[PDB]
Image (spheres, rainbow, N blue to C red):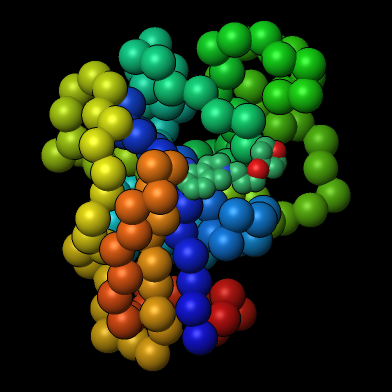
Length: 150
Ligand SMILES: Nc1cccc2c1CCN(CCCOC1CCOCC1)C2
């Protein structure tokens, strides 16, 4: 009973989280996930600022209202070579990664590791934060509040 959460650098408080390195988070689970990080789903304005500071990924994730990929550099296999905050328009499916926003984070690029999940609640799951440099932090707990997400 284990979940890996792959997390990125923060840019103006905004970061990306993948569950088990595969698209697998529902919109309701994304909100609970960010809450476990004492974070919220970013607004488009927050995300655009993060992008201006250096934030980009090659993965779809939720923000408040939309599913997006922030892109700085054109890449043919990432958001169809677009730049800016690319908005997913047409999809059959409901499960993606998530973006999260922590207001307490540094204002620009913070590429330090994440070493806590400060607002997870009591639970039976071994939750492991996995940073891009491989550093890991684990704790027993839960963050999902909706039964349909478990
Ligand atoms: N931040 C982080 C920490 C630990 C592992 C990882 C990441 C981000 C990328 N992520 C990629 C996982 C799957 O690669 C995707 C497949 C879909 O297209 C973009 C790359 C791995």
